[PDB]
Image (cartoon, rainbow, N blue to C red):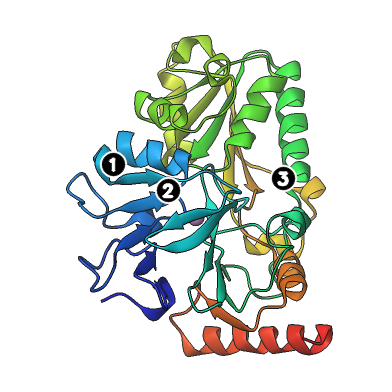
Amino acid sequence: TCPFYKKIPGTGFTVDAFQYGVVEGCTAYFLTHFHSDHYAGLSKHFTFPVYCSEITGNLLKNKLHVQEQYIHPLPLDTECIVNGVKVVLLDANHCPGAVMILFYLPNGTVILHTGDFRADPSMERSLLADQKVHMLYLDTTYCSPEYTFPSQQEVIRFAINTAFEAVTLNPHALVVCGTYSIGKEKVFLAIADVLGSKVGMSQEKYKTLQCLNIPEINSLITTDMCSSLVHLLPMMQINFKGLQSHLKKCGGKYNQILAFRPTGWTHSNKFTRIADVIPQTKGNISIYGIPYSEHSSYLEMKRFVQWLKPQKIIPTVNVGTWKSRSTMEKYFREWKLEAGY
Ligand code: NI
C-alpha cells in the first residue's frame, strides 16, 4: 500500500511509487531519478506510463529493460501537459538525470516535489521565481544542524591535489575510486583529468555511464583496464582485502594503491576540516573517505525553504519514527517564525 506522501492530491499521479503493485487511480507514474530506493519495483514487465527526464529514460530502457512504449521523457525548464495537468521538470542538483517536479493543479494549487536534491541559490532564478507554492514535498535527508559538510568544489580540490601529489612522487601508484550507483561522477572524472588518463571500469559500469549524456564521454572512459591508471570498483571492494586482491590482478604494473570512498556525511565531519582529513593505511594501501554530498546540508535546505515560503511542508525522508517527525516539524516552525511567513 502506497503511503500518502507519494501521492499528488487532485491528480491521478504518483511520485517514486513502483513497489506497491497497481496503485488504484494512478494514470501516470513519475520517477524523479535512477536510484534503487526510488525505482524499487520497476522491471521489463511494467505496463503503465512512466514520466521522467531523458537521462532517466535512457537508464530505464538499457539497464532495467522497460519497454520503449511505456517511457515518456520530458525536457527540462519547459511547460508540458500530462493527462490534462501542466507540469515542469527542474534540475535537482542530485545525480545525472535527477529532477524536481512542479505540478499546476486544476483548482489553482501549485505543488513542488523536490525528489532528492542538493539546494542551491541558483534555484532562486529558475522558473520557481515566478509564482507561489502551496505545498512542498521536501528531501529532508539532512534536516538537523549537526549535518555540516563542504562544497562539492572544495571536496574535488582536495581529491585532485591528493592524487596528483601521490602519483608525481610515485609514478607506479594506481588510483582506485569506489561506486555503487550513479552520481558523484565528478570525483573520478576530475582525478583522471589531472593524471592525463582515461578511467577504467567493468563493462556493466561503462554501459551505465554511456546512458548519461556527458559531453565527450568517449574521450574520458574505457573498458581496457591496462591502459588506465584510474580504476573504478564496486564500493564493497574498497577495503584492504579487496584492494590487495585487485593489485594482484594488475600484473606487477603498480606497487601502491591510493583509493577514494565517497560517502555522504559521517560523524568525523563534526570535528575535522576537509584540509585535515587523513587516510587509513596498511602497507602500500591507503584509503581516503571523502564527504561528497548530493543532498542539501541543513543550512542549504533552510535557505531554500525560507526563500520559497511554502504554506505547507511534507517531508519525504526520515518519516518512519515519531522523534524524527517531531524534530523536523520543530525546525520548520523556527524557520517560519524567523522569516515571517
Ligand atoms: Ni537519490
Q: Is mark 2 within 8 Å of ligand 1?
A: no
Q: Quadrant of residue 191?
A: top right
Residue count near mark 2 (Cα–Cα under 10 Å), binned few <14, some 14–19, many ≥20: many
Quarter holding residue 285:
top right
Q: Position of residue 318 (x, y in %)?
A: 50, 75
The disc, 2 or 3, on the residue closer to the chain's N-terminal end is 2
Q: What secondary structure is marked by label 2?
A: loop
Label 3 vs label 1, nearer the camera = 1
Quadrant where the C terminus lies?
A: bottom right
Task: Depth check: give the residue in front, 14 or 236.
Answer: 14
Decide if residue 96 is on the left or right side of residue 164: left
Residue type of the residue flagged with mark 2: Phe
Q: What residue would you read off at disc 1?
A: 64
Q: Is residue 235 visible?
A: no
Which residue in the protein does label 3 denote? Answer: 278
Kind of residue at disc 1 = Leu
Left or right position of 88 against 15: right
- Residue closest to the eye, 30 or 64: 30
Q: Is residue 87 visible?
A: yes
Say if mark 3 contacts mark 1, CB within 8 Å: no
Number of other residues with Cα within 10 Å of mark 1, as a class: few under 14, some 14 to 19, many 20 or more: some
Left or right: 252 in relation to 262: left
Quadrant assignment, res 123: bottom right
Query: Real-space Cα distance between discs 2 and 3?
Result: 32 Å
Question: Which type of secondary structure does the marked residue at label 1 adopt?
Answer: loop
The mark total stands at: 3
- The residue at which mark 2 appears reads as 34
Q: Position of residue 55 (x, y in %)?
A: 46, 39
